[PDB]
Amino acid sequence: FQSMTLRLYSYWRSSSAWRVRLGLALKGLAYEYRAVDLLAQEQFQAAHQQVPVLEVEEDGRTHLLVQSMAILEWLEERHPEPALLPPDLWGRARVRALAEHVNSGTQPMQNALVLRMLREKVPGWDREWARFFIARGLAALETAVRDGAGRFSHGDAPTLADCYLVPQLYNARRFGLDLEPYPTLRRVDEACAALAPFQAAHPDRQPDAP
Amino acid sequence: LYFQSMTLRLYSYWRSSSAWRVRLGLALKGLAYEYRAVDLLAQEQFQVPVLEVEERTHLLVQSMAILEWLEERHPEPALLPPDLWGRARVRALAEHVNSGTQPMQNALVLRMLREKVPGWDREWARFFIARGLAALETAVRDGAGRFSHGDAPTLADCYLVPQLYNARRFGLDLEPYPTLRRVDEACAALAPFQAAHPDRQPDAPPPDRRTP
């Protein structure tokens, strides 16, 4: 008998990895942190045309789970409490949509490879592009979150939606975006920041934070 | 009471890959729906998909959220397996497309690319689609039977099929993805896939009035 073990391949500043760190922390799940040298990896990838990976061992078999949303859905199914999705069908669809706004609708357009391609083609274009797409994504997210937010993105408890929102706002700040136009997002971000699991998952608390 | 009887209306554009995913979920579950055409081209030259659920009105958005709702509300036939590992694999295959491939070739992205550099949007699309399909080919190859996951259609095929159509649109050579081609062929022979294809949609133009 081999009871389940968790290992996360992570980079301190990766928003994708951070989402999964939030799911793990909110669920009270311990895991081995395995740092990936993402800056070296990206330099190599650049010259030649990834995290998170959640490695799970149980009963002598190993599973390598990838894609933040798939990993988070697995955490929610495998370890139900505390719940990061609401119990009702409508609320679940809303929370998944908020998460996907970020997962598919905002973050990909500020992918390191995307920005690198833009920068190699036209220097500086990468910054303009990231700012445009992140602001666009946040404007749409602000509207959607406002219609249904309580203390958090959905009602009065953290959900998968907050796990996507928080790292995306950090990236927005990195690109120098004014967050004043997203008051609901800022309020929710502040509520999350006061929670111990959010503090634990933050880039600055990770073993590979320089 | 979220399992009461309902009526469905899909806001769709014939060529929208995101809408196509939802059309596939509906067809595979045998669910009738009203087609509400949204002319994305007319409304460009001058939101899709939205699944409107009526019983009071709920507007469901984002292809993956809509498909997960369909799977919860109408569990049979299942487009996610019952085992948790298989669910994670299927969702990962879906997300490789949903977040890892399609966003890099969406309409606004392509437009802004060719606005700053003419011609480059199609080279870019081919680069990112190829990148995505290469990952899929390998991830699918470990666990595919006749389809992306095992021997029956799942959510993974709902994402794969429209993405391969877009690959062809952009003139990407599909020879390096033999597993994906075989899965595409298996899906294409099924009635629900035939029903959901762009060419069969109410707003589809004839071939001679289509853009590349």
Image (cartoon, coloured by chain):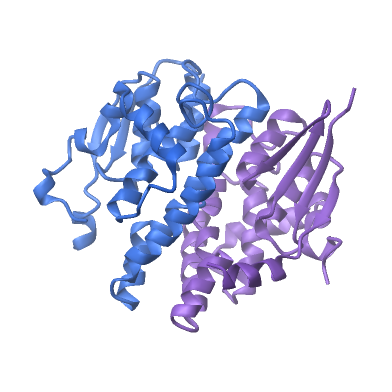
Chain colours: A purple, B blue
Residue B152 horizontal side relative to residue B170, left or right:
right
- Where is residue B119 shown, x and y percent of the image? 29, 71
Which of the two residues, A85 or A155, is positioned nearer the viewer here?
Answer: A85
Which of the two residues, B46 or A37, is positioned nearer the viewer here?
Answer: A37
Image quadrant in which the C terminus of chain A is located: bottom right
- Where is residue B195 shown, x and y percent of the image? 26, 27
Residue A35 horizontal side relative to residue A83, left or right:
right
Residue drawn at the location 31% of the way across and 25% of the way down: B189
Residue drawn at the location 19% of the way across and 62% of the way down: B45
Residue drawn at the location 16% of the way across and 51% of the way down: B210
Image quadrant in which the N terminus of chain A is located: top right
Name which quarter of the figure residue B31 lies in.
top left
Residue B132 horizontal side relative to residue A176, left or right:
left
Which of the two residues, A39 or A164, is positioned nearer the viewer here?
Answer: A39
Name which quarter of the figure residue B46 lies in.
bottom left
- Where is residue A143 shown, x and y percent of the image? 48, 54
Q: Taking B188 as reference, is A11 above or below it?
A: below
- Where is residue A167 shown, x and y percent of the image? 66, 59
Which of the two residues, A159 or A175, is positioned nearer the viewer here?
Answer: A175
Q: Taking B203 as reference, is A49 above or below it?
A: below
Q: Taking A124 as reference, is A37 above or below it?
A: above
